[PDB]
View (tube, rainbow, N blue to C red):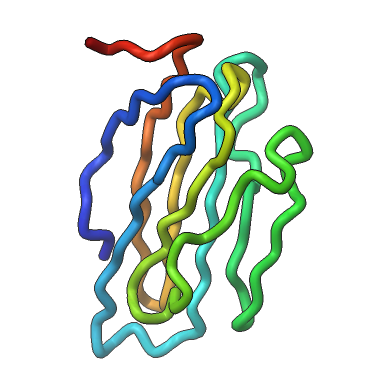
Length: 124
């Protein structure tokens, strides 16, 4: 499963947000590894929008237009147990719940991060 609970990350416009998603695999989890990150924007009604994906040993991005080029996995070895990603140059539009799904049949886990972006620094 994923090593961290549902959390809230508060950043400032322009900064970069690090969305942690580390996981441990069980001996039973013998199926192929899939890592999907979805987002439910606060500004609109869309829910569970695909942001980035790791399937069949390949990375697939370019799903959520407004987030183009600003999302990348942080680790250079996902299989090792780290699905974390970075959202660079945060904008107020990036506010919403980001979800990390890590699957290895029969294994499945997910984590929800509520990202908040503030015009200028301070959560004081």
